[PDB]
Image (cartoon, helix red, strand yellow):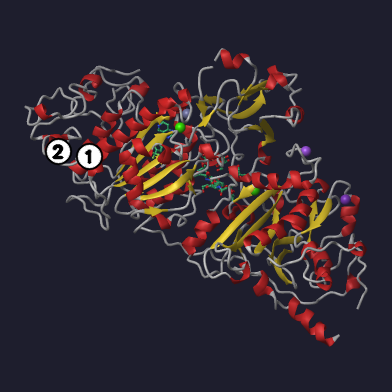
Amino acid sequence: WTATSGSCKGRCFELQEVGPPDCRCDNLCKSYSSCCHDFDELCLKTARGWECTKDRCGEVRNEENACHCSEDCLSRGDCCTNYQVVCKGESHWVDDDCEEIKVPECPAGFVRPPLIIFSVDGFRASYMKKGSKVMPNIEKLRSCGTHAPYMRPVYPTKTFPNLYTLATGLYPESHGIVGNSMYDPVFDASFHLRGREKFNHRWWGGQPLWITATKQGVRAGTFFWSVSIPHERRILTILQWLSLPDNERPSVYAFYSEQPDFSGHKYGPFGPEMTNPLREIDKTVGQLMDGLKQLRLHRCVNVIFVGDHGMEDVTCDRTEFLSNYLTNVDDITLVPGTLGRIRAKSINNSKYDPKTIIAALTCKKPDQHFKPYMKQHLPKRLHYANNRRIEDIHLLVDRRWHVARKPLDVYKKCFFQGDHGFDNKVNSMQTVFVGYGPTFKYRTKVPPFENIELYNVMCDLLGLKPAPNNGTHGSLNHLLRTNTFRPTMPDEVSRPNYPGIMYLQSEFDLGCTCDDKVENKLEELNKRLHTKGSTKERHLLYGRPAVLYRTSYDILYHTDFESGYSEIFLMPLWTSYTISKQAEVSSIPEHLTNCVRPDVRVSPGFSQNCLAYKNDKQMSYGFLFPPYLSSSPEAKYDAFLVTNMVPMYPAFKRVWAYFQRVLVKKYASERNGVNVISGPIFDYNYDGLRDTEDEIKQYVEGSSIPVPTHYYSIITSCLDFTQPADKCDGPLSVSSFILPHRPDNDESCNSSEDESKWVEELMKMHTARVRDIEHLTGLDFYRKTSRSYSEILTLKTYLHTYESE
Ligand SMILES: *[C@@H]1O[C@H](CO)[C@@H](O[C@@H]2O[C@H](CO)[C@@H](O[C@@H]3O[C@H](CO[C@H]4O[C@H](CO)[C@@H](O)[C@H](O[C@H]5O[C@H](CO)[C@@H](O)[C@H](O)[C@@H]5O[C@H]5O[C@H](CO)[C@@H](O)[C@H](O)[C@@H]5O)[C@@H]4O)[C@@H](O)[C@H](O[C@H]4O[C@H](CO)[C@@H](O)[C@H](O)[C@@H]4O[C@H]4O[C@H](CO)[C@@H](O)[C@H](O)[C@@H]4O)[C@@H]3O)[C@H](O)[C@H]2NC(C)=O)[C@H](O)[C@H]1NC(C)=O
Ligand SMILES: [Ca+2]
Ligand SMILES: [Ca+2]
Ligand SMILES: [K+]
Ligand code: NA
Ligand SMILES: [Zn+2]
């Protein structure tokens, strides 16, 4: 109930909302059917439109007009935004040459440069180039300020998840806005684009920018705008708020536009109809900037121009139907379109089986335009598992396609020509970033970055302490002129042991054998030095990874590789080796095929044993340092140490062996050497974070050898590929992956073929940031380089995407 009988007299666009039954006058009142009776009349005036004209200059104040051109407007804070240009002969902001803003030039009473975030829905990255000719205001922001070629959204590339991510710095699995449509089973309640359930606060987790500011004494403009408030009115309202008294005036503001998403859905991303909405957004930017110029705030405010996601060509004829795969299509509920989320229709149907749904959806048709995944098997880069609102079964839809349950869902809902929601590495999904202002750099291009990183920057811009989030604070310091955040490296928590030779061969009863009984003071001292770390400078190029949790581990040196060996997990946490451009690849000699050797530095009690692998009919083993890349027949023996072995399913070994035998050498040839760090990951609860021992769900049969859920590799070289990786003076280049350790290759529909036709494709899908691996392992990499820490943080957030230009 709303007593709509009160008035908005002197309260239009009030910041502090009022509580029912009292009627509202804030910028969401329309959305709630709660505005006082006179809100339209008073707060949504449109008379005479939005632009001063020569004749109106100096007019008598008619309170009825949408904006004013009368002499006193600048003092009331309510002039039309072109007032000074039309009436007072000033130039539009966009006609002004750009001049570096070295310092904020703010009116008296301003305690910090305000921030205005100008958000645009569905603003695909390539519009900056393709629409350049019709967006002069945005082009000026872009060219004069700081911009990225693109900004990467989060998955799913839908509006609500992305805007909330921008506002929180969190992945959707952590803020809880996991799609535009959702069912939460604990609440037993559904979130929809339409209607009122979406307004309950229990859906929206984390702490968004406007709460962060208020909690720390920084006032905020409201970030949500009811759809029916026209853009011109939104801009005028922001400008009005900027003329409030110091003690009342917000320091952070946001504008939202539904375009160009709205027209993109109708016409596709580059439909001829798309030019006009681009034109209209640009004009809105111009109004804002002219208005700031009128207020003498154009060299005071930081402005961010940012999109939530891009847009792809999608038509109703590119739809796959689950009725063409499933016998029991009525037994499931699908969240449809550019992603799929499946669960049972009835929690009382005990004949529901995910296993059979997944099998029926896997590689059943040659051209299949989606792939099914149990959510924990999704690429870790998606961070899309750890929320009860995310259904166990997920469909990753090919770009340009939809999935639906039955044909009838499409035509009893071709209408539309664009959509979005696909894999966030897809080129069409990429969106935009521009920063303009005294705190941003001048005429600066930065590399692409992920939208999770902006919350921290927005906090830096306002002098706020960010709430805990998924950004890496400091990784975007290169965008900023000032207010940079200077973190320290995290402290190492566990120091390693450095064991020497402590065990005789006969103390080991592991059930392992090796044909190695083949016996020189020249090379006997040499091998000693290798075991004491003499080649470590070669193989450990950026220092040892630091262990950020309490544990017991040993550093093991070898000729060709260095490792950090866990006494708890009985295998390495990390193995580090460097392969030059000139390295030769060799085979595992016939005589050593099944060779496994006791490590006389590591107790039998803290070692794996071969008998467990023999008795586990499902599980095999591989090596972290690859015996194929041994520097000499003699050094190859190090590679068969029990301390280099890890559990591997035979299906996985196909992947791993191709990686090790072919791809590492390929990268070394292409990148002029590479440094490789590889290791296990355990993430049985699919939270993105290192498991403790008690979370481990699977062990090699009859033993305490835990089974990894994934294997990672970090592959580093010199960004200037004229310098060898092991003698690099400057910035580094990285590519990494987190490969799922699965007992089959059902993910790869071409896996019956030779590994050259499908392995690298898999690996590319499971590309990762170094930071993803750090979260997953409790390790901190690149501790000892000659580069600044912020530069290293940027490197750790890098994702090698494998998309074209
Ligand atoms: C990305 O960044 C984020 C933010 O830093 C990282 O997420 C954090 O990770 C922490 C560890 O995973 C997690 O810590 C837990 O917090 C519990 C208290 O949490 C509540 O309060 C905070 C503060 O106000 C709030 O942020 C939380 O918000 C979550 O939950 C509400 C719903 O109630 C949601 O609306 C909201 O979106 C958010 O959900 C997300 O997180 C929850 C888990 O919190 C997930 O389940 C969701 O799927 C979703 O992702 C909460 O309201 C705290 O109680 C936990 O403490 C346990 O563990 C300690 C270990 O020392 C132990 O000593 C305690 O005893 C305790 O265990 C007891 O409870 C267990 C469960 O019943 C039980 O098993 C035990 O037996 C014990 O009884 C824990 O510390 C932190 O809350 C989130 N924060 C956020 C915002 O998500 C995230 O990891 C980053 N991602 C990556 C990949 O790095
Ligand atoms: Ca959107
Ligand atoms: Ca975990
Ligand atoms: K076996
Ligand atoms: Na397969
Ligand atoms: Zn859309």
Marks 1 & 2, CB-CB < 8 Å contact: yes
Query: Quick one: 11 or 627, which is closer to the camera?
Result: 627
Element on which disc 1 rests = helix
Q: Badge 1: few (under 14), some or many (20 or more) residues near its Cα, within 10 Å? A: many
Which comes sooner in the sequence, label 1 or label 2? 2
At a point 12% along the width and 39% down the height, the residue shown is 89
Could you tell whether 51 is left or right of 792 in the image? left
Element on which disc 2 rests = helix
Could you tell whether 531 is left or right of 508 in the image? left
Query: In the rendering, at what x and y percent does residue 617 appear?
Result: 89, 47
At a point 18% along the width and 41% down the height, the residue shown is 91
Q: Quadrant of the N terminus?
A: top left
Query: In the rendering, at what x and y percent does residue 597 appear?
Result: 86, 67
Occupied quadrant, residue 331: top right
**Disc number at residue 551?**
none
Q: Is residue 662 above or below residue 688?
A: below
Camera sees residue 259: yes
Which kind of residue does numbered mark 2 sit on? Gln
Camera sees residue 697: no
Query: In the rendering, at what x and y percent does residue 607 appear?
Result: 81, 63
Residue, disc 2: 84
Query: Quick one: 511 or 721, which is closer to the camera?
Result: 721
Could you tell whether 461 is left or right of 397 in the image? left
Could you tell whether 416 is left or right of 244 in the image? right
At a point 73% along the width and 19% down the height, the residue shown is 328
Q: CA distance from mark 1 to mark 2?
A: 9 Å
Query: In the rendering, at what x and y percent does residue 224 appear?
Result: 36, 32
Residue, disc 1: 290
